[PDB]
Each structure stands twice: as C-alpha cells, then as structure tokens.
Amino acid sequence: YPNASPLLGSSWGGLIHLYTATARNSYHLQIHKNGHVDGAPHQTIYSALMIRSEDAGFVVITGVMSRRYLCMDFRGNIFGSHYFDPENCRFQHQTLENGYDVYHSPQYHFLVSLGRAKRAFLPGMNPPPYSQFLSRRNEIPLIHFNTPIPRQHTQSAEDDSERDPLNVLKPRARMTPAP
Amino acid sequence: TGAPYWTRPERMDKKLLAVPAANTVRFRCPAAGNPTPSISWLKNGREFRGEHRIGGIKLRHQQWSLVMESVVPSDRGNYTCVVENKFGSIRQTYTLDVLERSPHRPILQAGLPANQTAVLGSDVEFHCKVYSDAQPHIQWLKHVEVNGSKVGPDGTPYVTVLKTAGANTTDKELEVLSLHNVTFEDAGEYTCLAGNSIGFSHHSAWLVVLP
Amino acid sequence: TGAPYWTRPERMDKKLLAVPAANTVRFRCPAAGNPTPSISWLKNGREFRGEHRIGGIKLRHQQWSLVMESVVPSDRGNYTCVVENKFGSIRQTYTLDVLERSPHRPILQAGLPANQTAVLGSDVEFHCKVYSDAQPHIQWLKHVEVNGSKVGPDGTPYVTVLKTAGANTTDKELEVLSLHNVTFEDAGEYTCLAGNSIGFSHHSAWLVVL
Amino acid sequence: EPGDGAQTWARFSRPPAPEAAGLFQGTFPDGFLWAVGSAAYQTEGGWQQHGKGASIWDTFTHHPPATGDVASDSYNNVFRDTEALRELGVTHYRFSISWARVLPNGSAGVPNREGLRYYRRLLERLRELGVQPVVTLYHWDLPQRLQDAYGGWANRALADHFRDYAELCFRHFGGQVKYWITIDNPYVVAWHGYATGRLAPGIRGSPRLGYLVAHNLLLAHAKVWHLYNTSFRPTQGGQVSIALSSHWINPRRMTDHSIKECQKSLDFVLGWFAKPVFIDGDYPESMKNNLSSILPDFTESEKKFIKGTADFFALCFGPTLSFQLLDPHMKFRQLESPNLRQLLSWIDLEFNHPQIFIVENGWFVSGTTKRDDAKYMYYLKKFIMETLKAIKLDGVDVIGYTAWSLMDGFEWHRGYSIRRGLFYVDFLSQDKMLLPKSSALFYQKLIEKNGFPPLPENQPLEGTFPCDFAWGVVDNYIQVDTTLSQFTDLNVYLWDVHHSKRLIKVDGVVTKKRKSYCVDFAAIQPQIALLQEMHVTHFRFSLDWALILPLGNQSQVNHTILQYYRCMASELVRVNITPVVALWQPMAPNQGLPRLLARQGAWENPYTALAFAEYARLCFQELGHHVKLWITMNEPYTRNMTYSAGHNLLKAHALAWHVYNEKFRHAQNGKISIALQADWIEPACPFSQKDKEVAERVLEFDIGWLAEPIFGSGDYPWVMRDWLNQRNNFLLPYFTEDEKKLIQGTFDFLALSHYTTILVDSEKEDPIKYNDYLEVQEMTDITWLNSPSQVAVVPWGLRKVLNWLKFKYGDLPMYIISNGIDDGLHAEDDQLRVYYMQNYINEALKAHILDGINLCGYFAYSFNDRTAPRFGLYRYAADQFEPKASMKHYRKIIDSNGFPGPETLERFCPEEFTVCTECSF
Ligand SMILES: O=C(O)[C@@H]1O[C@@H](O[C@@H]2[C@H](O)[C@@H](NS(=O)(=O)O)[C@@H](O[C@@H]3[C@H](O)[C@@H](OS(=O)(=O)O)[C@H](O[C@@H]4[C@H](O)[C@@H](NS(=O)(=O)O)[C@@H](O[C@H]5[C@H](O)[C@@H](OS(=O)(=O)O)[C@H](O[C@H]6[C@H](O)[C@@H](NS(=O)(=O)O)[C@@H](O[C@H]7[C@H](O)[C@@H](OS(=O)(=O)O)[C@H](O)O[C@H]7C(=O)O)O[C@@H]6COS(=O)(=O)O)O[C@H]5C(=O)O)O[C@@H]4COS(=O)(=O)O)O[C@H]3C(=O)O)O[C@@H]2COS(=O)(=O)O)[C@H](OS(=O)(=O)O)[C@@H](O)[C@H]1O[C@H]1O[C@H](COS(=O)(=O)O)[C@H](O[C@@H]2O[C@@H](C(=O)O)[C@@H](O[C@H]3O[C@H](COS(=O)(=O)O)[C@@H](O)[C@H](O)[C@H]3NS(=O)(=O)O)[C@H](O)[C@H]2OS(=O)(=O)O)[C@H](O)[C@H]1NS(=O)(=O)O
Ligand SMILES: [Cu+2]
Ligand SMILES: [Zn+2]
C-alpha cells in the first residue's frame, strides 16, 4: 500500500527558498549582506527567505541572514534594503496556472525576476525567465545559521623576543584610586 | 580513445530540478565513445527502470535521455546516470524534489471557531487554523452596531478588527484570540477571516456572557 | 510547379487530442516538396509566436514539429499547421482540448470527522469533505476488528467501504456516512480515503461507541 | 621518512575532546626516566681551578661583566648537588663533562687528573644515591686552543680530536654512565656561534660558515657514535644520541602553502640535523634545493657514516631556542608556538616512531625572583601534561623527561638576568647553598605521585539536592516589548460580504479601547513557553530604572512598562515558575540609571540613594504581590567602581531593604537581599604563606568590600582598611554609628555568583602586568580548560568559595544567582558548557552535603542567546530559538533533582520543612 505522505497545507510557517529555472540552469533567490540579490545554484543560508503576508495577496520577503527586505526600484532592479518601504517594497503575490508563483510590484507592474528581461505582468501572456518562482521548504539546519562565529586574533607582542608565550600572567582590569 | 565523454557539458547544469506534481521531468546525459557506452540509471544509487513507477517511464537510447510523465510526490531523491564501457565509466547525479502546489482558497478547520458561553468575569478564547500554501493573511472581526442596527445602508455588516496579521507577529499567536475577563459588551459574532491570492474564507462563532 | 505534400500522412488523421493537464504535447506536421515549404504555425487568428503562452513554445525544423511543455487549460483551441511554398500552401488543423488534472491530493477538510459517542445504541454521522478540482475517488474504510492492530503485515486490507466510486461519489452528497442503530460493534478508529492520479489523502481520529 | 608530519596540523586541526583537555589524568608509564639536567659552564664555575684549560666561554665573557668565572661554584660543592638530587627524588642526572677541564693542554697530552677526579667523585656520589647518570660530552665549551690553532669547529680535522676526548670518557665513566649525548643543541652551536656571532666563538662569518660548521659537527658526532658502537658498546651496553632541539610552528592561515612553509621551517631548524642521523644521511630536500651553493654535501661514504648513529631521540624544547634564539629566516613568516604535544606527534610521525627523550625542558623566570616562582612551575606542569597527553592520547614512545637547570647559573647570552633553576642560589653569597624553589617542591610531588592520578577531591558525588530546591535560569537583559497585539484598532469598519471582504473604513466613528488586559502583550508567551520547556522553577530577570522612571523622580512614571513587568511576573507565577527580580544592574550605557541621575555623578550624590529608595518602594508596591524574591542590586562591579560610589550603593541597598521590611513584609511575605559576585582567588604556590595572605587580601578587596557591611560585622573589612592605611590612601569612607546600625543586617539570603578562579602570587617579576595597587600578580593555570573568552573552567572553586563564605559570614542560606560560561563556536563549544555545568553543580552538591552549608538555590546563566550573546542555553538563529545540548543536560539534572545515582526512586519530602526558604524565621 502507498502509505500516506505527510499532511498537506500548513508548511509556510518558517523559512522558505525561492527556486527557479529555465531548463538551462537552476537558481535559488539569495540576498547578500551588501544588498545584492542573485541566484545561488545551491541552498545557501543567505537564500533563506521568510515570506510574511500583510493583506490578502501582498507578501513581504525578508531573509533571515542578510536581515534585508526584498525591495525594488523604478526600473525593476531587485535589491535588499534595511528599512521598510511599503509603497515600493511589498509585492502582490500570484499563482500562475501551473503551480508556479509570480511576485509583481502593485505599482511598477514589473515581475520579480532573477534575469535581465523584466517586463510588465500581462494576464497570462508570457513571463520573463527566472520569474516563475517556486517555494521550497528549508532543509539547512539552524546550526549553520549561527555561522557568524566570534573569532578575533591576539597577536600580542609580535616581535620575535617574547618572554611569555603561553600567557600564564593574565592581568585583570581594575581602577587605580588616584585622588 | 574509447573513454566516455559528455557530448554537451552546457546541458548538464540542472543539478537540483524541482517541479510541481503531476508534471513531467526530463533528464539527459549526452555522451559518446568508441564503442558507445551503455547507460545505467540508478534511483538513489539503486538500479531502477519502469517497474515501480505507476504509468511507466521511457529510456530511449537515441538521445541519451530519461523522461518521467505525471510525476508524483513519491519520486523525490537522487538520480544517477552512468555511462560505462570497457575503457571508462563515469556518473552524474541529478536531484528531483517534486513539490505539491494547491492554489485554492484558504481552507480552515471545520468547527473552529465554535459557539461559546461564559460566566461574567471568566475568560474565553477562540481558535481558527487555516490550511493554504499561498501565505494567507488572517484577521478577526467582531460584529458591532455603530449607531442603530448592526447593518449598513447596503446590508453590509459593521465589524471591528481585533487581531490582524502584521509582519512582526508569527502565525502561532494569531490562531488564538484570547478574551480575558469578558464583560457584557463583548458578546456578539466573532469571525475569523483568512485571505490569499485566490480568495477569502471566514468562519463565524457566537459568544454569550451570562451574569 | 506541383503543390507540396506530406511524407507521413498517416499521423495527420488525428485532429483531436485528449491530452491531460500538466503534460507536454507535440504536434508533428511533416511535409515535402520542391522547394522546401516554410515551417509556420497559427492559432485560430493571429500568428502563434512564443510570447502568447505560459512557458513558451518550441519549433523543430527537423521533423517540422511544434511542442509546448506543461500544457495549460488555456491552450485549448484550433491550431493550424500552415506550410507555405511559392507553388501554393498546405493547410491542416488540430483541435486540442485538455482534460483537467490537479497538482494535489484531494484536499481533505481537516478536523472532519470528530469523536462522537454512540452510547445507549445511538446513531452516528461522519463527515469527509474534499476540495478537489475534479471529482475524487473516495472510499470510507470502516475499520475491521481483526488482531486489534489496524496495521498488520504493513497495511492489511481492512477496507469495508459501503459507498464506493460512482454517480453518488461526488463533492455534493457523499460527504456524510450515517450509521444508524449502532450497538457495540464498531470500536477504535475509522479512516477516510480520497485519491486521484497523484496520491491518497487518508486521515481520521478516534471513535466512541457505548 | 620525510613528509609524514605534514598532516600533524591536520590531525590537530579539528577541536579536541572538551572533557579530556583539562580534566586529563593518568600516571606515567612504569620504567619512566624522571630526570633533571645541568650544564658544564652554567654550573661548574672554577674557570681556572686546578689548572683547567680555557673554553670558548672564557674568551667570550671576558671582553668579547656578566661572566661565568664562578657561576654556581659546583666544581668544589659536589656534595650539595647530589644532596639536592636526593631531596628532589629524581632517577637521572643530566650533567656535562667539560672538554677544557679534562684535556687542558691538548688531546695529545696528559689528561688533567683533578678534573677526572672530580667527575668520578660526582659519579660515585650520585651512584650510591640510586640515580643513573646521563652525561653529555660537549655542551658548547670548546677549548680555546682548538678555536685558535685549527680555527675551531670550522676545521674538519678537529672532529678527530673530539673522538680522542670522547675516547677517554668512554674509558673512564663507561661502567657507570649508560646514556651519552655527543653534542648539545648543535643548532645554536653552528648558527649562533659561527653565523650570527651571539655565542662563545662569535665570529659571525656568514650563513655559509654556519652550514659548513654544522657539516663538521655532524661528521664529528658520527665519528664518536661509531667509536662507541664498534669499540665500547659490547662491554658497557649504553646508548648515544645527539641532543637535537626545535620549536613548534603554526600556519598563518589554514591553506596548503602555509602548511608546507611550516614543514619547510621545521625541516630547516630540526630536520637539518635530524634527517642525516635518523633517516638517510643527507640534508632535507626542502632545504637542499634552497641553498645549493651555501651548504656542503656528503659523499656516499659520509651518507652511510651519518645514517643510523642515534639510539634514542633526544629533544631540547625549552627557552634556549623557542622564542629566543630561532632566526626569523628559519621561521618563514609563520607563527611560532611552544606546543610540546604537537611537536612530539610530529617527531613520532616523521622519524619512524623513535624513543623520544625530552632531555631539556622548562621555561625561565626573571632574574630578580627568589625561591618563589610560579610562572616556571606552571610552564613545567603544562609541558609535563603535554608529554603525558602525547604518551597516552597519541601513543608517542617518550622514555623520559628532564626539567632543566637543577640549580641556577649562566644563560650564555642573558647573563645572570634569567633564572631557570629548580633550586635557588644567591650569587652574591659565598656559601651558595641550594634552597628548594616552589617548582622543586612541585617536581618532588610529581615524581612521588608519578604523574597526575585521579584526586579524591574530584571524584563525582552521587546524591540529590534537598527538596524545594530553587532550580532556575537567568536573563537580566530581558527583552521588553510592550506592543499590544490585539484590541488595538479602535476604528469601526464596514465589511461587505458578497463581492468583498475587502472591508472599508467608515469615517467619523472611533470606538473605545478595551481594558488593557495583559494577555495582549505578544512578547511574553514565547519566553514563558521556553522556560516551561527546561523545567526551571525560578526565572530571574532585572527591572529597568531608566524606563519605569525616565525623568528620575516620581513625576513621570511609565505605567505601561510596569504593566508589562507585572504581566511577566503573573504569567511566571501562573505556570509554577516563581520569579526573582533585580532592582538595579550596572550593565547599561550609564550605570543603569536615569539620565538625570547619570548626569550628576550618578553614585556620588546621596540623593541617588534616596531616589533608589523611592524607586524600590514604587517597585515593591507595583510588582510586590506577584514577585516575592527581591534582589536589590545585581552583581555590582567591585573593581570598576570608586569607594564613595560603593558607600552610597551600600546606603541605597540598606534604604531599599528597610523600605521592604517596614512596609511590605507583613503584607507580601517575600525575601530581599543583595547579589554579589564571588569568583575564587587561589594562591599560585599552594605551600607558601605570602601568596595565601595575598589571596586573602584580594578576596577581602573583591567580595568582603561590599559584603561585610551587609552580611558581616557592619564595618568595612579590616584587611582592606589596613591595606589602604599602610599605602596612605585615606580614601575609604568611615561608617557613622547610624549607618553602621542601619546596614549591619540588611539581608535575608546570601547570593553569590561564581564564574571562574584566578591564581595570585606575591612576586613581582614583570611590572607591566603587575597590580601595583594591590601588590598582586594575577596568573591563571594553563592546564585548565579555557572557553573561547579565555576564562578558566575550575569546578572546585565554587566549593572553595562557598566554604569561605560560610566560614567568614556565618551560616546563611546561599543562592547561586549566576553561574555559566560562554562559547564562540557552535559545534563542540556547547559540550564545554555541558561539562562545566555538570561539574559545577556536582561541586555545589558536594559543598551542600559533606560541608554542611545551607546552599538551597542554583541559577544557570543566560536563559537565551538573544539577550546574552555567546552565553545562552537557547541559541537564537534565524529569529528562532533552538535548545542546545546544555539545556537538555540541565533539564535532566533538574527533573531528577541532582545526581541520584542508582537509587533514583525516592522523594521523601512531603510538606518540606527545610528552613532556608520563606518560613517562620
Ligand atoms: O536532439 C535534438 O533534436 C534536441 O537537441 C537539443 O535542442 C537544442 C539546443 O540544446 C538548444 N540550445 S541551448 O542553448 O538551449 O542548449 C537550441 O538550439 C539551437 C542553437 O544551437 C542555439 O544556438 S547555440 O549557439 O547555442 O548553438 C540557439 O539557441 C539558444 C536558444 O534556443 C535560443 N532561443 S530559441 O527560441 O531558439 O530556442 C536563444 O535563447 C536565448 C533567449 O534569449 C532565451 O531563450 S529562449 O529559448 O526563450 O529563446 C533565453 O534568454 C533570456 C536571458 O536569460 C535573459 N538574460 S538575464 O541576464 O536576465 O538572465 C534575457 O536576455 C536578455 C539579456 O540577457 C540581457 O542582457 S544581460 O547582459 O543583462 O544579460 C538584456 O536585458 O537583454 C535581454 C533580452 O531579452 O534581449 O531574456 C532572455 C529571454 O528572452 S525571451 O524571448 O524568452 O523573452 O536564453 C537565451 C540564451 O542565451 O540561452 O539563444 C540560445 C543560445 O544559447 S547560448 O548559450 O549560446 O547563449 O538556437 C537554437 C535553435 O535551434 O533555435 O534548440 C536545439 C533544438 O535542437 S533541434 O535538432 O530540435 O533543432 C536538446 O538536446 S541537447 O542535449 O543538445 O541540449 C534537445 O532539445 C533535443 O532533442 C529533443 O527533440 C528531438 C525531436 O523532437 S520532436 O518532437 O521534434 O520529434 C527528440 O525527441 C523526442 O523523442 C524522440 C524519441 O523518442 O526518439 C522522438 O520520437 C521519435 O521516436 C519515437 C520512438 O518510439 S518508441 O516506441 O521507441 O518509444 C517515436 O515514438 C516517435 O514517433 C518518433 N517521432 S519523430 O518525428 O521524431 O520521428 C520524439 O518524437 C521526440 O518528441 S519530443 O516531444 O519529446 O521532443 C529528442 O529526444 C528531444 N530531447 S528531449 O528530452 O528534450 O525531449
Ligand atoms: Cu487545485
Ligand atoms: Zn608563589
């Protein structure tokens, strides 16, 4: 017997990655700390978006490592911001007639794309490449989301005449009482 | 030499191929050799042909391609193509992750929220849980009367929102509406309304407070 | 001088194709003549170029075919293979209609049914609503009290459905199973099977009887 | 074979075991050679006694002061050296036979009878003792005549002369001695004697001269070894090697080029002398193709002559080459490192698993220190632990150990300004009697124990904490977020429901706001759920003064913040988590105070104390019915704080406590006291009394400064007042009778917070890191585990500080308000937290059971990782809280109530009557 698969429905609470392809290459949408948005071939911790809805059909895409927001400009160039831009950085979501998502700005009409042929969203005429996204659940463990690891250097007395290499004598900060 | 070699390397870049269910997938490993190497297609590293797949698969040798029509969720995993001959054997592993896309109105649990009664001074809570893949937005509305009746000039009811879906609140803390120390004025019709790109679905409940 | 003709006219007798949704389709319209006729297509009106469909179209000049991947119900219509030569042109038609499919299991309305109590020989009603685009394939599968465990040799056939697929199996009236005058003869849990060409939705909860 | 050690960094790249790194024990293997060494010129002196010759170290320290004419006067004090050896309890003396004394006039001449008589006296004195001697034939003291006539070691005929000298040694002491070393540290005899000129010959010709003289050194060593093998071994049965020496090195970055450069450096320094004698007979290829025209080449006969002429692998890892005399060119811009264990692993891999023998080891001390040294003791302890780890954890055939310089003496370029002796001796005296240093006592105990066996004071204890124990967590940077989730939109909307549910606002109507019942606060429930998961029983957070009263006075109370805190307390109580709050904490941009107070000294004005009294009264009357364990001031900084500030802090704490006691005790029945910070201060040398009283002074300067007025007698600690009066620093305020009566008893439970342990020694050896104000030298042991923040994991410190508190301030109920360590990584650093928490809880249980203290609480630090970064049990990644393994182990300890062992089937506490919690007093 074909044992039942896990329950359908509630799978959007948590991190998602926006996969897309054009039968020549496959990319997951990824937001970089420097405000760069690009397609990573694999699932990177910088590609972990968290889509949250405000109205009925108007999503905002955050990403949990860059801390950016997926925001847009007047010529359609996707980028990442740090402060909310509700008039420009909040995309109307839509689901095409083959299960593929599309995200278009409500005022710019330019579909969210990973390519360089952004266009207006006509009612099912033709989409630009890399604009028909698909949400895939996150499989990256959260331990790799703590990748920022405090690691500084000591380099104490870099001259080649050091008299205490293992740092046994460790002075402790104080306050000398000079009136 | 007779060692196998890929005919087109630019056609072998779709490492992770994901598709909505009931669709068709098309792998190919175009190679050549002297003599032409044979192909072994392994599902998760295990030999596979059109035997455990309902509907059958095609493994035509003329194009070095494997097609799968009407894919199903029970097809996820690695798919390794091997081209082998007496002068070399090489492999390439694609990955298939078939998704399940259901573009319908937000379907929320039946019987929730339900009619409730409470003694004045107690506390109640209403529950509504939605099931839709398009990131639905959930709010709660209490039916109130503004000046006269609870009905507007066009028959449209008067409601006040109680808890909407902001970007700063998770969806675990929105599926419950907690009325603490319910008074007499907070006894009407509470509707959980959910909306995605397809449409809106709402369920109503009634809370009655007794002295 | 003479008008061009086809190389394999035996495949041109099928104007109608009952293709399923979410499946690619190919239209083969081969022809031959002196000189070679142009490979052109049309869609009951304007020129059927690659920007009037979701996913695009591909034209193959080897066997003169037109292919469209992941067909969509909006693709229904009357395509025309028109091959133009200086010595006349050749017309042929394709009437394409798409059988509807659905990229999901029958969406079981969660929470149905409940754990009612059939104490003192009362009656029980059970609910199962599936929000599928098409008409699903639904069985009830009231459990069988054998060995106690509903799963024996990895899915033992405990199916005892009394309302199978048919004209009465739709999304309008078969939502409710009514067991009347229920004595102590059905304990444990029930199930609810729905399915189509993709998968099986199967979920239920505990039951109380006396 | 060459290259087998190139992966040593790779083998040590991965993090080691976080429990066997500092808590590593195990006796050394039986048949171990515990040794203590010495040199010839460093210790003998008597540069012209009994007609000895002139070395090259008597024509270098004499106008090339600080000479070695009489360094330790051990030429005639032969009895005291062996007396010190017997008292030390050692089984191998590693001394040197000086070339110039046994053959003063010439090898082709009469040997000096007096020098041989002295050496035979030494051998017969240390043979009846029970010590097998180890001798080195050449310890840099080449005779001056051989330096002048033939040009020193540069000549190739001089090698033969060496053999002659060696011959007579083999004829005389062959019966007694069974270990010989032909050359000591040939690197600093071929390089710093003939290339840079820093040592005795000091001609600093060129690198080419150094390489040629090293070639001649290798030839002479081969000649002597073959003389021994062919003529003397079948009659005396001994071993001969060459005392090689090396450092450790680490790559700048974990690439392959850097690793190969490190391997090249190690080949340049040590393989340069080790490969020809141990592997094949020629110089390493990493250096042969780098100085082709600089270094000479062996013929095939020479290649067969050098290979296999060393029985064991003598190693000299000390301060004579590491970090002092290594030429930076041989380092190849990598990072030098004194890691003995990795070097031993590299030797074992590279040179075909030989019998390593550390024939010289141990760091140095500044030249002014008397018999109380503690940097040397801990460096020696670390090196011995590294040797033990290499023997056990990696299987390296180490057959002995030799701490260097039994007694002080010359240092060959550092004069008398450096002390390396296990036994102190004052060169300004005339008797020069060996006084045992602290390191001498440590070595005595280490030999007697024969390693580091499991101590009885570190065995885990099985047993349960008493019932009603306060198991809790701590989050003092609580994330206040008073936004209201529901019922916050007052507008009336019109909700069309036919072609719609795009509800539209209708203007002109705004309804009233529902009463702000505190379920509305969204940022409360997740924290309560996280606390509920780990089964804690006391959450501890801190109130914010700058938010409740932003202006400073009672005219601008922010009631919303108080409502949020009252909900936090109510929700905590509702789920059986009794809350503990702290009124003030010094961790804030301005001392945890309102800006108005912070801009007026913020602790010098007594009005700050009065304002804190008013604020404490307000917080007692707002949150007082839910919170019932109050903490007045949470871990004040006892170092980065003045004395008037501490006085006013004490006055404010007394004011707040009396406000509670006189107003809100018969109505709320809570408890209130202060929470200090009590890290343990251990004397560095466990047998000397100066650092003991110095540790006492540091303790009473850290703990007893803010605790004796409250918990103790009432006045400031007497040691602190004496110390401040002796230095004429009359900056300690005096307590008036009114203040002494006010403050003497403002406490209901002692509350400490232990994190680590610091050792203190009372010897000034480098005033740069000295603490002149307290006259303390603060060190840390390096055999302890260290968190990425370089904080010491010391379990027994908690028990020691609890016993000290009970002994000093009577018998009081004690809470451990905060006790936790931090992490920098994510994979294995949390395992360090698991180990530290388990051992610290075990030590607290030990202190409770078999010491009698009334410890009835414990609060693990850092509830989550968002408020306290690098510290939390609940890591905060991608705006999601995931538990660490430390949380699960802590919960396992909690719900089992300690460490019950096999008898985990008892409760035995119905209606608990342990009088430390809220009882009838
Ligand atoms: O073999 C064959 O045939 C084939 O082959 C192949 O194919 C191919 C190829 O591949 C291709 N190429 S690629 O590239 O892709 O790779 C193509 O090609 C060609 C050429 O070559 C080329 O060139 S080159 O140079 O490359 O060379 C070209 O191309 C390309 C493309 O194409 C184009 N286009 S088109 O349209 O033309 O196509 C272009 O493109 C471009 C564009 O642009 C676009 O694209 S598109 O497409 O869309 O157009 C894109 O773009 C984009 C971009 O991206 C963007 N950018 S960004 O940045 O944003 O991102 C934009 O752009 C832009 C720019 O960029 C900018 O700038 S910047 O700088 O900033 O960047 C600016 O802004 O600007 C802009 C603009 O726009 O401007 O945008 C765009 C978009 O746009 S739109 O318009 O869209 O809007 O992309 C681009 C690119 O670049 O890419 O170009 C390209 C180039 O590339 S490169 O790299 O160079 O660059 O051209 C072409 C042409 O031709 O045209 O195609 C080809 C075809 O071939 S043929 O021969 O056909 O002719 C393949 O393979 S492979 O491997 O090689 O690959 C495949 O396909 C194959 O095959 C198939 O087929 C066959 C047959 O069929 S039929 O149907 O006809 O028949 C077969 O089959 C099947 O099967 C079989 C068997 O089975 O066997 C058969 O059958 C038979 O048999 C059977 C048996 O039986 S049993 O029983 O046994 O079973 C039987 O049954 C039967 O009956 C029989 N029949 S028969 O009759 O045959 O006899 C069957 O039938 C069949 O069937 S089916 O159906 O299935 O088919 C085989 O098998 C198959 N295979 S499969 O598997 O597939 O199926
Ligand atoms: Cu559907
Ligand atoms: Zn000391």
Image (cartoon, coloured by chain):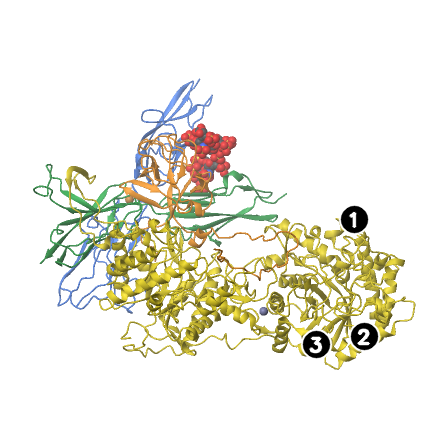
Chain colours: A orange, B green, C blue, D yellow
Q: Which residue is mark 1?
A: D292
Residue nearer the viewer, D798 or D335: D798
Q: x%, y% of residue D153?
A: 84, 58
Q: Which residue is mark 2?
A: D119
Mark 3 CB near ligand 3 (8 Å cut): no
On screen, residue D607 versus residue B67, left or right, reads left
C60 up-or-down from D247: above or below: above
Percent of width and height locating residue B63:
49, 40
- To which chain does the residue with label 1 belong? D
Q: Quadrant of the N terminus of chain B?
A: top right
Mark 2, other Cα within 10 Å: few <14 / some 14–19 / many ≥20: some
**D792 left or right of D221?**
left
Front residue of this view, candidates B60 and D693:
D693
Q: Secondary structure at mark 1?
A: loop
Question: Which mark lies nearer to you, 2 or 1?
Answer: 2
Chain letter behind tag 3: D
The three-letter code of the residue at mark 2 reads Tyr
Q: CA distance from mark 2 to mark 3?
A: 16 Å
The alpha-carbon separation of the residues under discs 3 and 1 comes to 48 Å
Q: Which mark is residue D85?
A: 3
| Residue plotted at (26% across, 53% down) | D554
Residue D85 place in picture, x, y as percent: 70, 76
Residue B64 lies, in percent from the top left, at 50, 42
**Front one among D756 and D748:** D748
Give the amino acid type for the residue marked by disc 1 in the picture. Answer: Ser
Tell me the quarter of the picture where residue B6 sits. top right
The answer to whether the beta carbon of the residue marked 2 is less than 8 Å from any atom of ligand 3 is no
Tell me if label 3 and label 1 are in contact, CB under 8 Å.
no
Q: Which mark is residue C179?
A: none
Same-chain status of marks 3 and 1? yes
**Subunit bearing disc 2:** D
